[PDB]
Amino acid sequence: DETPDECVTRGNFCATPEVHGDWCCGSLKCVSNSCR
Image 1 (spheres, rainbow, N blue to C red):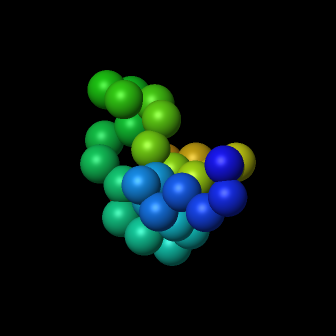
Image 2: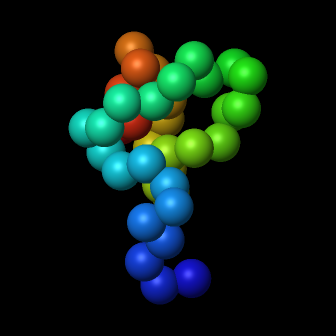
């Protein structure tokens, strides 16, 4: 790992969380369709 741009960064839009659970970089959470 170094700089995975394959994950969605903080403040960016995330799709419905429960279906994938993973998507946002690091300790970011998919909530309100946004990673934080």
